[PDB]
Length: 362
Ligand SMILES: Nc1nc2c(c(=O)[nH]1)N(C=O)[C@@H](CNc1ccc(C(=O)N[C@@H](CCC(=O)O)C(=O)O)cc1)CN2
Ligand SMILES: Nc1nc2c(c(=O)[nH]1)N(C=O)[C@@H](CNc1ccc(C(=O)N[C@@H](CCC(=O)O)C(=O)O)cc1)CN2
Image 1: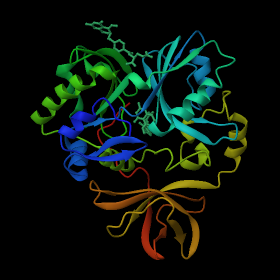
Image 2: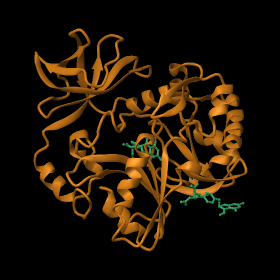
Image 3: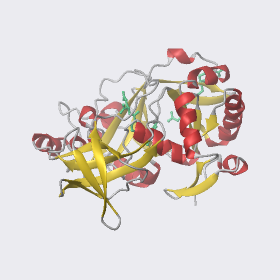
């Protein structure tokens, strides 16, 4: 398996290692619950160095990105980041991502671990008619997520610049624990927080400095187990589970990141798709402690309406929760049934999204 620059730190910390997208990563250090609560109460630190980063350099970096992604990048000012999806010609979602507008001549793309290769090939095969150069810097880049209501106050003493000046989905090049770091007020937890992008060689030092501070305020290093729980609670999507090329953005609640008033890959297909949205992604709260898995069929009074996409147990709400792709006819309040292996029906209630929202801003 691939190992991030912090692998040794995780092992030394006694974490339970698991295989995620071909990466040897920590599922948890102490327990998933304890780590989720650290994220919800103080601060949880995640090693997300398996994520990929692409660099787009050149006079036409802006127009190129605006052509590739569904969201409006054409006017995004310097220092701003933006969440979006990238679609194929048929409007299917290739991946979701975060793009940083460094300057008119430079943009950074952060994508999911499992799709680095796919994404990079897609982006490069589309740069032909743009004055840009696309490069993959994943192999030498590390990324740490410092999330929680106490994230800012704990991290500040290691940063040479004031964090308050960094707005939600904004960033700035600075120095953290003595090393060059791109600090952005972003996250995948629903709490306030930051992500620290830096050269892989400096990952160990920054992580150790941060660990020293966590212990001071009862914070915790957090693994992928907690990462999934918190993102599900926050109701953020996980590519490959909640959406893929077989779903367009409108079907999974991402209509807000699609600006049809501009030209981009998948534009025409999405115009027609918008006219007939037959599916929707709903939030479910199941009865009991069993956790639903992707693929489990979802029924309404005996009739199939869709299937589970993501599932997990939420210690924040103390309930088994899930996301499900169902027909447009399903509505909040509906009593549905989830078919577990062996034909066992588990009751589920459709609730309003999101499940939970913490200390997050804009
Ligand atoms: N920098 C970064 N890039 C990344 C991730 C990440 O965690 N961090 N991802 C990790 O899997 C994937 C994208 N998944 C994500 C899904 C939702 C949100 C998110 O913050 N959604 C807020 C956005 C609010 C706004 O733009 O104003 C929301 O839906 O409310 C972020 C990443 C790929 N790229
Ligand atoms: N005291 C001091 N402060 C300083 C600097 C310095 O040299 N000394 N810097 C001097 O410049 C900046 C901090 N250093 C940084 C330089 C680059 C990146 C950065 O954006 N790195 C990207 C590079 C790849 C890309 O842009 O595509 C990355 O982390 O991947 C972050 C911090 C601002 N403050």
